[PDB]
Image 1 (cartoon, rainbow, N blue to C red):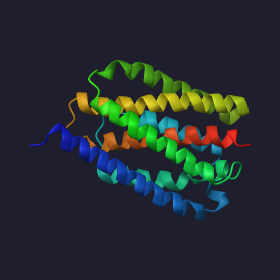
Image 2: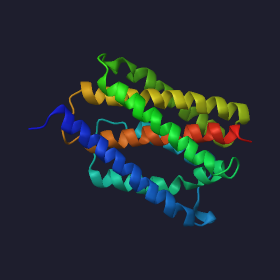
Image 3: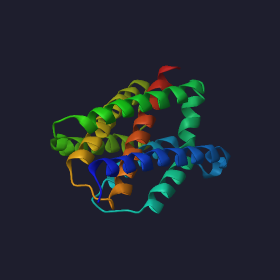
Length: 207
């Protein structure tokens, strides 16, 4: 017999693990040949689309989530490599740090606050869809410095709210132990998408 704590603690545990696993992949990704790396524009929007797509009421298993963490890690290297080659490698750690305290604070506030934030789902879902549209647009008609900057701020807001909203809904909704991987998967996609948005913002700002 589970409690709402053990369920939540297990989700946060898997989440931490996905982060580690991805980081392993990020290391390995530095060895992928140039002929096998995807364009920056495509990778960036890909993570948005996945964050929407993997946010389905379908239940997935741990094997899927950890493999997705490892392989996304590898493929997201060209992003880290780009914004570090225009602002210095220190901006990667800076972006990680901000993403970290943001998640840690908004996550905690979200998991303990009294109100039920369920009414945000439509606003949030429309927002990620708008981010995706601009991201697809960016592939065929590249945005300028101020535009990508403004975009990253919107994205920073949207996913910051998603971290708060997910930890809140994890508390309020009926979450059985079979929905543990997909909740962890979503939190991972929140984190990663918030990381990319912050990296692009601070990357551009330092050049």
